[PDB]
Length: 121
Image 1 (cartoon, rainbow, N blue to C red):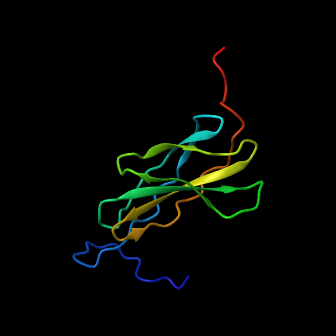
Image 2: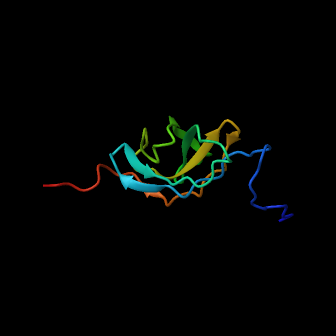
Image 3: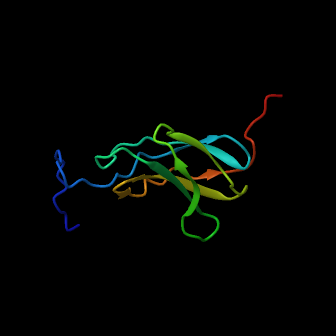
């Protein structure tokens, strides 16, 4: 553990980078993409510049990959396209500011992209 200061206080000069945002959700957006919605908490003191969404293949071996990027601070939800059907994987969110990038948000639940969800009729 080697715990450190871990103390929250109103900085004045020496600021810090953004922290890992809440856990992103998974919704049915398409057969090749999915609607992801996250909730940012800390920005390190400065205004978030852009976010980062990454995923990981469970059925297939391979570290986390990069889905999208260059997302605005006002956009807390986007459609992650470019996925492979029949391949289970998770998603995450990262905050990048003029100070640096944030930690890897908790790995949301595993979503198995099968198709365009249900139908109307």
